[PDB]
Amino acid sequence: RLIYTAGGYFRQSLSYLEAYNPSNGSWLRLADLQVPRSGLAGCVVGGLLYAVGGRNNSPDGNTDSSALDCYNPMTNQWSPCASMSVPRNRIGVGVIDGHIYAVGGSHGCIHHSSVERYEPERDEWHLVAPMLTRRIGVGVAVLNRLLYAVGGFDGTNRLNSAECYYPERNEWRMITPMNTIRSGAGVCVLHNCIYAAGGYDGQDQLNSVERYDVETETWTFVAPMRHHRSALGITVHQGKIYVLGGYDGHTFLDSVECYDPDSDTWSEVTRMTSGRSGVGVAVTMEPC
Ligand SMILES: COc1cc([C@@H](CC(=O)O)c2ccc(C)c(CN3C[C@@H](C)Oc4ccccc4S3(=O)=O)c2)cc2nnn(C)c12
Ligand SMILES: [Cl-]
């Protein structure tokens, strides 16, 4: 029912949790994160919203986060969960069969290839097989109970490469690379395709959008977004992609755009209450 945006960055890391309602255009401000964080990811398991990793960039210092925190819309409260094995800033996450996969990200100058999986029933993290590539600012999506890690930055180069994790083999394999180098792209799934929207290539923030068809193993460009943006939040709500904020090399954007795959068009839907980048985004039910 609602698109939740958690944390992000403008001047410093943010604690905001706000929920947008596509049905009426309204934004609600909800309970702040306990710790400000940018470069985190959001996901939903069993109706609960999780905020994963990131970094607190504050005037008092810069601290990468290994934190997992859970928001209950029914109570409007955040609860701490078990922390990850390592801090993971500029993280990507995916959910498969009620488990959260935390992928890549940085801890200071360490750019992680490691991956770990959270089991809400046990409140436990366990490492799984590492990716073949170190990736921070990595886009993650899940399609047909397979996990995809797309683009990012390896410590030296921004990447067009992507790879797939096969849970029952505990194994990563490269897939077809994207046609575009993208770090901090928005990555999501819609129908049978993984979409990669925007990002940064070391020179420019991008408006281009391409999608990987798992059946054909090829990437194809769709219509570009109205705004160039890196470190955007992205989610799917009722068969449409929504992209939230990000950075265009000039402004921390408040723009929210929506993609209709049937007309292959992007349109402006709303503005966030303030411009920000590096948010975590996910969809769950209305609070209380
Ligand atoms: C080094 O410059 C950049 C890096 C990244 C990547 C990382 C890389 O490729 O080296 C990236 C990917 C994901 C995330 C979340 C971030 C960090 N966030 C975006 C940046 C532009 O804004 C800031 C600034 C300060 C603190 C935190 C953030 S962020 O919103 O979390 C970067 C994206 C950029 N877009 N414009 N510039 C100048 C960028
Ligand atoms: Cl950062």
Image (tube, helix red, strand yellow):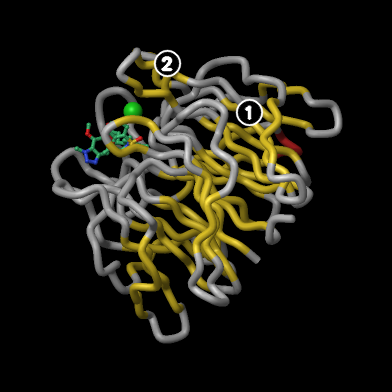
How far across and how far down the image is residue 20, in percent? 52, 62
- Crowding near pointer 1: few (<14 within 10 Å), some, many (20+)? many
The residue most toward the bottom is 263
In the drawing, what numbered circle is on residue 286?
none
Crowding near the residue tagged with mark 2, few <14, some 14–19, many ≥20 C-alpha atoms within 10 Å: some
- For this rendering, which residue is in front, 4 or 175? 4
Residue at numbered disc 2:
63
Residue at x 35%, y 21% (from the top left corner) = 58
Query: Is residue 211 among the parts visible in the rendering?
Result: yes
Specify the amino acid type for callout 1: Leu
**What's the residue type where badge 2 is placed?**
Thr
Q: Tell me residue 118's x, y (percent).
A: 72, 30
Give residue 217's position: percent from left, percent from top. 49, 60
Q: Secondary structure at mark 1?
A: strand
Q: Identify residue for label 1.
A: 68
Figure quadrant of residue 60? top left
Residue 115 lies, with reference to residue 196, above or below; the image says above
Q: Would you identify the image quadrant in which residue 38 lies?
A: top left
Q: Gap between marks 1 and 2, in whole Å?
A: 15 Å
User: Is 186 located above or below residue 109 in the figure?
Assistant: below
Looking at the figure, which quarter contains the N terminus?
A: bottom right
